[PDB]
View (cartoon, rainbow over the protein chains, first blue to last red):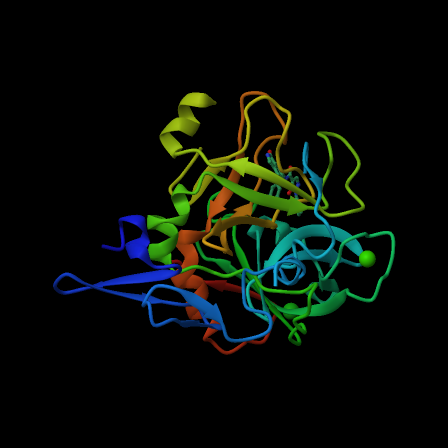
Length: 57
Length: 247
Ligand SMILES: O=C(NCc1cccc(-n2ncc(C(=O)Nc3ccc4c(c3)C(=O)N=C4)c2O)c1)Nc1ccccc1
Ligand SMILES: [Ca+2]
Ligand SMILES: [Cl-]
């Protein structure tokens, strides 16, 4: 599953035995109940540009 | 950077400038508050490790605006497989003496998991490369941080369209118009995926920047994710330079 379109995960993807997949998020993010989306949990998460994130907020 | 544009202040907040006795040495990439990724070759000729400084939040080298944060470099970690003066395994992991403070102008780039980087990010065509390096071959370096969007080649295509190992990748243009350059080595090749940016390459070196028939060569960071992660969990060792087994 993870090799195709990232398993539908926004960030990281692990295959498990069966038709099973788990998405994961980097430190500073949490996984939403959709099981795919990652949302920041800190002010300055990695890989986001604050002046552009606040221009879109 | 040849043929790019000024990175608007704060839009490349992971970029690091490395200085030796106040002089520009190389670039780097912040990946956490105490860890910077750069290129091994940047350190081949350092005599006194005490005079190495990393600067975060830099933009215009002509002025001080108060967003800069300088740190001493406590550890420079190089793979055992790197040979000075060459391209293969051209990566260094730098431990700062004290964390930087994250701000609107100082933010780490995400170091991706290996699988994600190999399965997903390796197929994103365009990525950004940045630095204060030469604006032209045999030209002056830049005073404001520059950035360039470059397309990545599969290695078979690089060899055709032009040694390139599994520890490298090519990206850029073969017409001499757009490239990274001397003074940019060690800086980031950053790749965007679904709203977040990731480290996929390090500006390395070859015979001459912006040369017709040749692409830029980047260290393939996906090969080193496990190596980097293990080192970031390790305690520091006396003596700045550390050669660490690879793999
Ligand atoms: O002298 C040694 N290391 C100290 C050092 C420190 C900092 C920068 C350098 N350093 N000097 C030249 C360049 C350079 O041209 N970088 C490039 C950047 C981007 C691109 C290209 C080249 C390219 O061709 N296409 C894109 C560079 O980065 C060297 N080692 C050593 C040399 C010879 C023998 C043994 C060891
Ligand atoms: Ca400045
Ligand atoms: Cl030392």
